DNA sequence: ATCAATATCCACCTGCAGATTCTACCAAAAGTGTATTTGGAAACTGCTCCATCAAAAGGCATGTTCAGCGGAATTCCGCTGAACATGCCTTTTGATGGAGCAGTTTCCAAATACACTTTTGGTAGAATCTGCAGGTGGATATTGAT
DNA sequence: ATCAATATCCACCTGCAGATTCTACCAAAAGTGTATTTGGAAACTGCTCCATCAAAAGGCATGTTCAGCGGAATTCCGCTGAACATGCCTTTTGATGGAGCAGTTTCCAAATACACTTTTGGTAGAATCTGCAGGTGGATATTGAT
């Protein structure tokens, strides 16, 4: 059974280097990631259907992130993702 | 434009809702709500418009947004 | 001759009237304007299918008519008959639309 | 042979995500962009909530973040609060909040 | 002969099946699912039209219009629960005035 | 495409002398498409929970039980189970 | 002569107390039974992972706590401080649980 | 035999819940009304939870069963497998 | 109870907007047929964790008494909705150029599908590590009686 | 306001469960590298239907007046909340047989993947048909004034 734990723990260390996390909380965190994960892929999924497109791209992903997340969160979310895409693209 | 939504009109809605006596300060309280509703819904419809590379919000664009809002509407797709 | 109707006789009459019809109760032109105005703040120079505006209104009025239903209930719960803002306020809060 | 995560400048697992996208059957195909973008969004979000939780832990003089901290962080931020307005964080409790009219005296 | 008939149905079993796979719901789609589902779409349909046709009659009307569908739905506990978050354009509302609001007889 | 014709057919078995307005048919179409999406989605999820690759009538049934109110559900199950039976017994 | 706290002085302390913790407020065993009773009078011969019984409890109190807040507001709306069934009922009606 | 377990939710217990809910004063009738409300909640979730269980042809209601049934009813629980 | 003014129905009437019947065209469906593949049931079974009996100790639920206070009933009165006839300014209706929303074609960047090789993140299980829970005492409020 | 009774605060204290930390096997992931396929952007276009506009339509803004609604104020009353005694049922800690979830190999009924073929449902342009919406009228129920 996979889990986003080690990655949560990494991100955790970056923001608050000396703070730990109980297992119960890491579970709540794993639940959080999977929750949002499905939610976005869902909006992405339908969006694609509504347009008779068979592939989910960074463009659907992005629209979903906009439909899904509130003001400030969405704004910043797009950046990070665009950022990553750009860096992933310009690297090969 | 917001005041374009008139007292008589608002009064009518309220009566369809079974409201018998209406306070004066309700008309402005009403408009505000109606505004947040449209904002919340149009915002999502327009997003559908743009994702589709269009310049015209379509009835389906609104249908889709409303569903996401949990305000499923029958009669324009559904 | 001096003839008048008592407060409410006209109301209840209006209630029965509108609860029977299904027509939209807001004037379309003013509505459509407010719609576009709101829209323009999200994306410039847009167009609307005659039908998109119709859905929006149909959805709008519907939402309201129902919110007035919960408000009258809130007004009544407080042993009143005049719906006030705090009644709308309370309904939207329990609806999860506020806090 | 770097990983796509590193190649994207990420901490979350780009490959894993692109993988789940397939097994979740959301569309016939999934372009290489989606997973990169989605892992980023996922990562960004966990950071935002961990930042906020981490402070709550600190505020309550604790070192290890526990569910309550997660809860305090979410209910205190307008946005994470909306993003999760229908999520129940177990063992989180509620935010201390007493209605005015319930307090004593007069002034 | 069409699957609809083999299943003795008025609805399009072939179409339903088509929509199921093309809808990305699963990797594969058994042969009966679309039959079953079509069977279930048909029945729910008949149910509404039934109650809806009755409303028409109870109005001295022979053609079913939106109102007749709205009335038929919010009057049936179950259907009403199912469409509990659906707006029927041009449906209006059920006639109802709070007791406490009726004239003081 | 649209379920309209099938709707109209079903309508006639029920109320043979009753007709329907376009706006009503449109609503009926919206109704069919809705339910279709809701039942399908549940089934889809169901399969995933059990790590299954196929959506069978098994799923459609459970889905239905989860989606429709008791009585409504009961009949819907019946109608459905009947079709599969009828269908399976034929060439 | 002996010290005596006025009504509501303890209540506030309890609100402050309980609002400060996160422990489940219902006897664990009695809850497991109720769960098993209900489950059983729906399908016999069923078993429960301890975590399932806990997820239900977590869900259930989370629900009740939130429902009590709505109730509290509804009462306050009526200019009272003592919540009553009618308050719970108004809340559930607006919430869409018995509308 | 299991019976009247709903009375297992004591007056003390219901009171603590209302306290966390910020309620100061409580009507004597609140307790039974509440038991009723709780019962309908538990009924609704268990049913779906158990529908999921039978479908999986299992005899043990799992924590996921409960988490799936809760999401179905829009009461998503983080902490028990999602 | 008695008019007087309206509001409200019921029955009949008809023009036309929108439902309907008729037809030829046909591309996307839907069905039939053949060959190949595979999801997942079946069966043997290791092994997790569930139901359960055991028992002791105290944290708590139960039940009583009693007074304090909150809610309901009532009277009072200032204030604001609402009914109403008045008079035009905004909405509605049917007519018209033209802007995009869709239909068709082209063809390449990008996504399968598949063979191998390499990196790793779950993990059985060891042993060591460490925040904080739960206990204690004393300094600091917060209450309530006077 | 002064003081007595109580609760909240809180920093120190340390056994200890739950968390950090390996050593390592590794089936599964993830990554590398052709070979093959194609989904959908991009450019060009016909044609709806949408933004615009003048004209005939018709609902809203407006000031008066007063009925009546809602809150402030004053009560008896009863039911809720502290406080307290008593003692039961839950919680705690284990051990335990074994039900049944879950892993692995076995394998065919059923689903997939074109291919060839026959039907059918949507689109279109014409013509013909008809449920019912408003309009009229005259009867009567409703409401309000006395």
Image (cartoon, coloured by chain):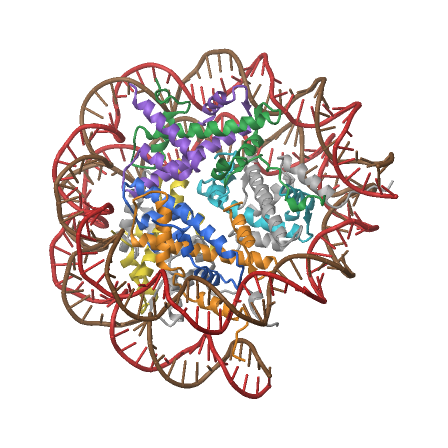
Chain colours: A yellow, B cyan, E green, F purple, G orange, H blue, I brown, J red
Viewer-nearest residue: F67 or J2: J2
Quadrant housing residue F2: top left
Residue F53 visible? The answer is yes
Quadrant housing residue J145: top right
Residue located at (59% from left, 25% from top): E57
Residue located at (50% from left, 47% from top): G97
Viewer-nearest residue: B23 or G24: G24
Viewer-nearest residue: H27 or J142: H27
G63 vs B36, left or right, is: left
Q: Could you say where residue I127 lies in the image, as x and y percent from the top left?
A: 15, 68
Q: Could you say where residue B4 lies in the image, as x and y percent from the top left?
A: 66, 45
Residue located at (52% from left, 71% from top): G9
B67 vs J53, left or right, is: left
Question: Residue I76, relative to residue I21: is it above or below?
Answer: below
Residue A37 visible? The answer is no
H68 vs E93, left or right, is: left
Q: Could you say where residue F72 lies in the image, as x and y percent from the top left?
A: 44, 34
Question: Residue J118, relative to residue A73: is it above or below?
Answer: above
Q: Could you say where residue J107 lies in the image, as x and y percent from the top left?
A: 14, 32
Q: How many numbered callouts?
A: 0
């Amino acid at each position: 059974k996979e889990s986003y734990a080690i990655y949560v723990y990494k991100v955790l260390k970056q923001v608050h280097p000396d703070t730990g996390i109980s297992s119960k909380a890491m579970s709540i965190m794993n639940s959080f990631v999977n929750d949002v994960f499905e939610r976005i892929a869902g909006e992405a999924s339908r969006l694609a259907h509504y347009n008779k497109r068979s592939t989910i791209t960074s463009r659907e992903i992005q629209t979903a992130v906009r439909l899904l997340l509130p003001g400030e969160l969405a704004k910043h979310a797009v950046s990070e993702g665009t950022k990553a895409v750009t860096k992933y693209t310009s690297a090969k | 434009n917001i005041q374009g939504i008139t007292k008589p009109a608002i009064r009518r809605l309220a009566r369809r809702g079974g409201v018998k006596r209406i306070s004066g300060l309700i008309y402005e309280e009403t408009r505000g709500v109606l505004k947040v509703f449209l904002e919340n819904v149009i915002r999502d419809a327009v997003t559908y418009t743009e994702h589709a590379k269009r310049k015209t919000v379509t009835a389906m664009d609104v249908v889709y947004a409303l569903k996401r809002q949990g305000r499923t509407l029958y009669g324009f797709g559904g | 001759k001096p003839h008048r109707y008592r407060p409410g006789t006209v109301a209840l009459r209006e209630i029965r009237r509108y609860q029977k019809s299904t027509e939209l109760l807001i004037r379309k032109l003013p509505f459509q304007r407010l719609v576009r105005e709101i829209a323009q703040d999200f994306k410039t120079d847009l167009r609307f299918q005659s039908s998109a505006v119709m859905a929006l209104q149909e959805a709008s009025e519907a939402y309201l008519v129902a919110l007035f239903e919960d408000t009258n209930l809130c007004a009544i719960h407080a042993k009143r008959v005049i719906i006030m803002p705090k009644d709308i306020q309370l309904a939207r809060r329990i609806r999860g639309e506020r806090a | 042979a770097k990983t796509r995560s590193s190649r994207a400048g990420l901490q979350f697992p780009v490959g894993r995500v692109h993988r789940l996208l397939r097994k979740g059957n959301y569309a016939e195909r999934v372009g290489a962009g989606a997973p990169v973008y989605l892992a980023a969004v996922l990562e960004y979000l966990t950071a935002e909530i961990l930042e906020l939780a981490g402070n709550a832990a600190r505020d309550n003089k604790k070192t290890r973040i526990i569910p309550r901290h997660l809860q305090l962080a979410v209910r205190n931020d307008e946005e994470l609060n909306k993003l999760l307005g229908r999520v129940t964080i177990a063992q989180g409790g509620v935010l201390p909040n007493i209605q005015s009219v319930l307090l004593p005296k007069k002034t």
